Amino acid sequence: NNPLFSPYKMGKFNLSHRVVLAPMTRCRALNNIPQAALGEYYEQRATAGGFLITEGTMISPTSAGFPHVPGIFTKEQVREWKKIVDVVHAKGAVIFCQLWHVGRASHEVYQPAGAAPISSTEKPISNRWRILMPDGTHGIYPKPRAIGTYEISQVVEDYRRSALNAIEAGFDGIEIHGAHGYLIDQFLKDGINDRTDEYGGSLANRCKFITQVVQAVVSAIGADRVGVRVSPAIDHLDAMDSNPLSLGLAVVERLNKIQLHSGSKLAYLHVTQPRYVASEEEEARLMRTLRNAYQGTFICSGGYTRELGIEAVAQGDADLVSYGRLFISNPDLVMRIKLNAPLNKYNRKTFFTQDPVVGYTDYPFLQ
Ligand SMILES: Cc1cc2nc3c(=O)[nH]c(=O)nc-3n(C[C@H](O)[C@H](O)[C@H](O)COP(=O)(O)O)c2cc1C
Ligand SMILES: CCOC(=O)/C(=N\O)C(C)=O
């Protein structure tokens, strides 16, 4: 029996299997408005009792660092998301919206009035990394503006309002993108956060921002509708920490405490495998250490295959396994994993293009 097809109770959500659509930016949401193409894409991948997480979704006008990514901060966006959620729900799937602020991982071209992007720090991402521009060229990450505590409270409110908007659109819940060197990770990582106020210095202070964000969304929509994604060890956008395992455990402690205070568990903790990029034992150590420390559901992501996903669930390393790239090219990935059917190759060249069909909805199902 395939352990990926054991049912799982993710809080009040009864999942029929443990294969999850990982959140993936695809850049088809023209002008930050969800489009009908997204509805077709998510519908193709939805299964009865399966869990889907959307592409990262803007919480405010300053939260983007990619072209044509959806927002959920306007009523127009909420109206269009509702059409997509309705088609996914008609297939019996559960869907969460990932709330995403990129912080310093942006460019003047993506910011209102060409202003600098915001961060914990004035330190830019280094020139080892370049940003995808709307014309398909690559640009230079600029120096961000370091925000004060009033503005931090405004950003927390943007997460809270976006969570309420997601519920209004019919989403089952939201995921906080606290990973991958984006805004929240720019507060978490000691390689980035050079602040001397209450949001920097100590590990406890560096965890303040994520704690406040999670508390705000939990208060607004309930813990069982909130998932949290982190990546304490990741090679992405110069987001390093001197002690990744202690950073991860400090975040896990905060999430455990939020749950005890709220009297309810979060939907899940979602952790990226350190092997994933845009020793193996230290990486496996870290994943299992975080899972064992967290009082709740654990989703693993990053480089998983059918075999590795089966092993993760069978060995108790994770409750759910999210797949990215293979879900791009296999709309029926769940069925293919169930049948052990051969998988289709994916085309990286069309990961972030704008076409509503090509490289998006035209990967074939099984015959
Ligand atoms: C095209 C693409 C876009 C992605 N965008 C996001 C994103 O918006 N938010 C996020 O948390 N992770 C994002 N990721 C990481 C994925 O959620 C996932 O963790 C990763 O793809 C898993 O590894 P796999 O592709 O080997 O299955 C993205 C990955 C890809 C390939
Ligand atoms: C490498 C880790 O970063 C990611 O996967 C990502 N978003 O989180 C994108 C847009 O690629």
Image (cartoon, helix red, strand yellow):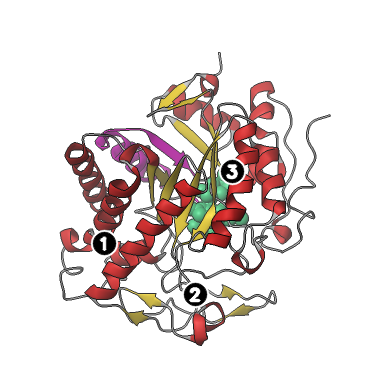
Region of the chain picked out in magenta, as a range: 275-301
Q: Amino acid at mark 1?
A: Phe
3 or 2: tag closer to the N-terminus? 3
Asked if residue 184 lies left or right of residue 326, the reply is left
Crowdedness of circle 3 by 10 Å Cα count: few (<14), some, many (20+)? Answer: many
3 or 1: tag closer to the N-terminus? 3
Badge nearest the viewer, 3 or 2:
3
Residue bearing mark 3: 85
Distance in Å between CA atoms under marks 3 and 1: 29 Å
Distance in Å between CA atoms under marks 3 and 2: 28 Å
Residue sitting at 23 percent across and 39 percent down? 259
Q: Can you tell which quarter of the image residue 66 is in?
A: bottom right
Residue sitting at 67 percent across and 65 percent down? 30
Residue bearing mark 1: 209
Crowdedness of circle 2 by 10 Å Cα count: few (<14), some, many (20+)? Answer: many
1 or 2: tag closer to the N-terminus? 2
Q: Secondary structure at mark 3?
A: helix
| Label 1, ligand 2: CB separation under 8 Å | no
Residue bearing mark 2: 106
